Length: 126
Length: 126
Image (tube, rainbow over all chains, first blue to last red; front, side, top):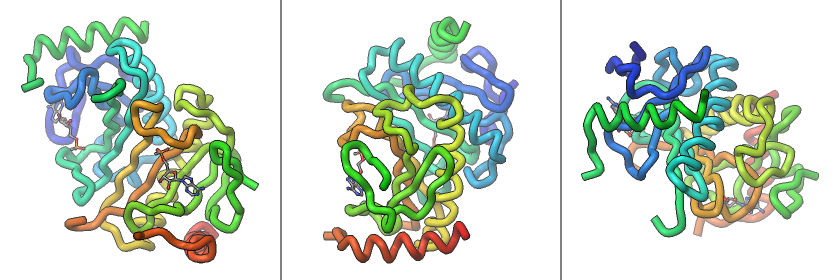
C-alpha cells in the first residue's frame, strides 16, 4: 500500500514510514543493504517536493543510513539521488539510494528474502 | 570566511549562504556547474548533523540544484553525498555534490574564474 512510481509496494518490504516519507528494500541491491528512501507523494523531480517533504526525506535518509550501515557492517555510506532522465532515473519517483560502504568493494532475491530483510531493519526503528 | 574541512574558503567563490548552510563552486569541476552544498558547521559524518541542519542542507541543495541546472543548461541533476572514508570522502566535512546533467555526457581553473562563476550564480538567489 505504498506507491513507487507506477508500482504498488507491499508493506512487507517497507521498513520505515514517517509522516511524509518511507523506506523500502531493493529487489536488486547493488551492494548488501542497498535501500531506497522515497517521499510518500509521487513526484518525479526533486524540485517538485515541498520544503517539508525535503526536510523529512533527508532526515529519514539520515536515520535509515545509520541503521543499514550498522546492520550490514559497512564503515561508510553513499547517498545518491539521480534526479531526472539524463541522470539515470528509471522509476519516475524521487528517491535516495542509500548504500553501506566498506573497505575495498546475481544478487537478485525473492519477495520473502526482501520481507525478511525489511523485518530485520524494522527492529532498529522500534 | 567559510570553513570547509580544514580549508578556509574565500567568500568570492561562495554563491549562497543560509542560516545553517552554504554553497561554493569547485576548483575541480567534474562537469560544468559541479557545485558543493555544505553545512556551515564542520561535521565529518552525516549522522553528526542535527535535524535542523539536515533539513536546511537539503532544502538549500534543492535551490542550488535548480539554479545550476538552469544556468549550465542541464536537463537533469545528480546529487551524491560520499559519507565517510570507504565512500570516497577526501575532505572531512559533510557536503553534497550537485551536478547538472545533460543527454550523453584539464577542467581546472583560476580563483578568478571561480569567483566569476559564483557571481553569475549569485544573481539567481537575489
